[PDB]
Image (cartoon, rainbow over all chains, first blue to last red; front, top):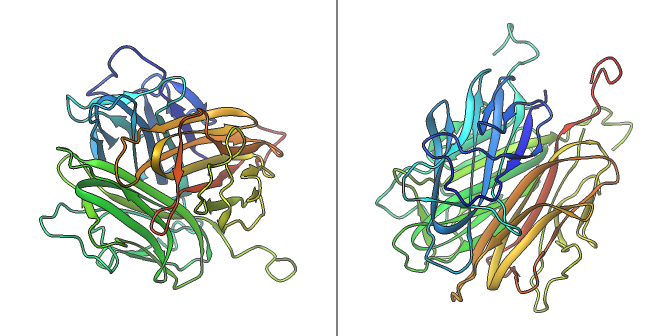
Length: 143
Length: 143
Length: 143
């Protein structure tokens, strides 16, 4: 089975959509259309186990984010921004089992900490892909 | 073939098991049981090439960790903790070829540097998965 | 289909090759020979969607790097080095669609910022792998 996407944040002078999925509005690859660049949500169509990774630039404020499945945090990440003149970085990742129509997204989970960033020479990316399908070959006999 | 897992660290007031595998005791997904959340070790059952990734929170002390195969470091990672009021972050990852019964785990490789952390809004995750199997289709004729 | 590699940087007292691919000269796994440890370039032989990840140690200078496809940046990453006594860290990653003979590599994209590092207990790794092939099963009828 095939399911994969990767997207990055556009540069922005406004604060990032918070307490809601964070859109990564600039798509690198989304052949199945399983990622929605308007909403920032990945929607599952193939049941299976997936890897998700965020590689973020942090600037002007600390960054906290959650990887979220169906409104609940899978895993949470944080990088302190110590008032430095140039950006820092934060990556997070996890695997999760999904069923069709389950949704996964990135969300800032605490108020102050929305320092995610992108610029000419920095980016913040969100990627996800199916590692194996849970439609097994002998679905009735075994499993 | 199928082999994947992902797990995270529980919050702890005690120092992390060191000079021994680091348990990530809270399992996100381990359908084959190839990861052992008690020991922190992944044990291979399908020969092949695997990706492993650690996404760690760092707090109160710097963090050094090794990704280890059969007791020897594959790759080593480090993040300085500059006495900041809130956590920093450290990710590491690599691919490795494994044969059945090979074991992979995370270990703190230097004494002082055991600042791995988890809390209400931070986590440290360990994930791994088979990318392709080395049981080829024409195993005798070629390869 | 099978395509994967992972490699790490050797310790060096000289500045890293810049404005050119960065060699990760120490190979962990490259069964297809799709990665060239001499040039630092991955060359595609199977069309499909790939994940690439860099997990770098940063020391003595800030680090900027781009993940590059055919001479153009896919995504750019940065970590400030605040003059600390010990290293910091920077990870970056993205997915991209490739066709045979396309090349992917890591490059430092800005002059001052070449603080990538490796030592006895730190590494910088570059990994990439095919997630799914774009040689579909019904290539004419559909797609």
